[PDB]
Image (cartoon, coloured by chain):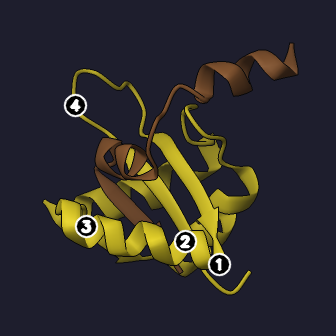
Chain colours: A yellow, B brown
Amino acid sequence: PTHVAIGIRYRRGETPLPLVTLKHTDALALRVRRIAEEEGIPVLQRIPLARALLRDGNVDQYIPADLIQATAEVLRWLE
Amino acid sequence: SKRRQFHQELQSSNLRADVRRSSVIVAN
């Protein structure tokens, strides 16, 4: 799964839960990261979460309950 | 059907569009 890029959205008030916006691997995952630089979107490395998100997370749906803890940490780190 | 979510989801013109929707990208 060499490269992984999961997009997460949470704007407090619009989303009750963080919601997956995109899931990409390999070349598209790298394309996502380069676009994210150009758009001012922070790219955080969270390997166990990224792997889990890849497997469990579904685009345009809220994050799994199992990944609420780990997703909070990501957002929390950026505060 | 299972196709309905996909169609609904496929109202996104750009990869950049989806990246811009995002608050944060989680990578490995």
Residue furthest to the right: B1
Disc 1 marks which amino acid? Asp
Image quadrant occupied by the C terminus of chain A? bottom left
Indicate which disc residue A12 carries.
Answer: 4
Secondary structure of the residue carrying numbered label 2 = helix
Q: Which residue is mark 1?
A: A26
Which label's residue is closer to the chain start, 1 or 4? 4
Residue contact between numbered discs 2 and 1, judged by CB atoms under 8 Å: yes
Disc 4 marks which amino acid? Arg
The answer to which quarter of the image holds residue A42 is bottom left
- The CA distance from mark 2 to mark 4 is 26 Å
Indicate which disc residue A29 carries.
Answer: 2
Instruction: Tell me the subunit letter for badge 2.
Output: A
Q: Are marks 2 and 4 on the same chain?
A: yes
- A54, B18: nearer the viewer: B18
Indicate which disc residue A42 carries.
Answer: 3
